Image 1 (cartoon, rainbow, N blue to C red):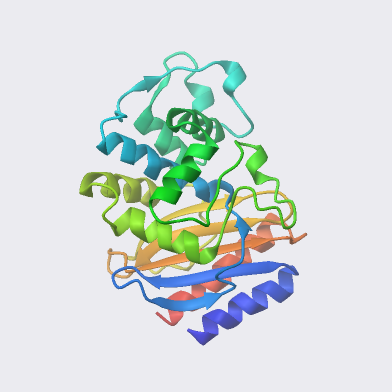
Image 2 (tube, rainbow, N blue to C red):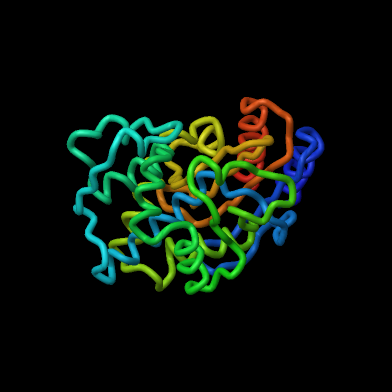
Length: 263
């Protein structure tokens, strides 16, 4: 809706930074709104959803088991590891690591999971072989959050990310069970509170994953909808701003309010 597009434009002026945006019908794949759809933005922790899609594909193929337990050392722990830092002794299952990565944003979780699939280059190969030749992952946590201006490393485009999420959640790539688990992790997101969630009416479904990085980068990917079922995917990024995290959150939430209002 135009009003939504206005909010996105207004967000771009106010933050003084590029904002990318895509609305997408989940069923039909039709783009409902767009803004800078073919420009690149840092993915930040929104990559963690793609990462666990890759993991789930290995699960389907029998190269991985969700209950397989991984131990690690205190050295392995990188900045912001709220869940993995609690299990140095017992270790964590692959499923637990993906829950930590997606619901809580756990960075060491993401690194251990990257190790399981072969690293950033192999995540990119996975994305490539599912028809996303745009999105690329190059580094690990925390360095993938660097957001150097015009750096192509660790980026996606709104339209590539919207496309890839719709294929992961509803496409033929993963088994029904693995696509249910992936959206189940996203529905259980605990660190995306002040963003799109803040705009939802009671009884609306939302599965999402947010992200934040250096130089004002912020973002969220989401499959949400009225009456407890999702029906649309929204991808929203921004990088370059000098704004506080609080103002970036409020801008996203304001954009969320128009999307809802004009659903």
